[PDB]
Image (tube, rainbow, N blue to C red):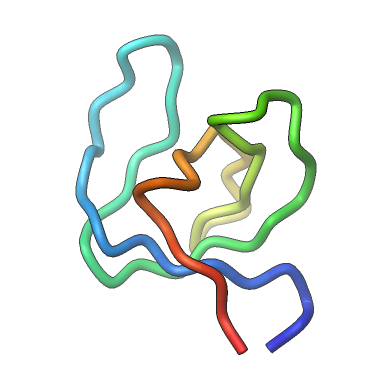
Length: 60
């Protein structure tokens, strides 16, 4: 896409440290990147959290 679009192939609704919940095949937009591992993305609910980049992928 381009509009900071990332898909979560993995699942982890959990929240070890206030992480961002998601499943396999979820859509999450890339907002900011406070960390090098976890980025602040927005799930399909305007929920901004630190989603794992290694758990999600980049869209076209």
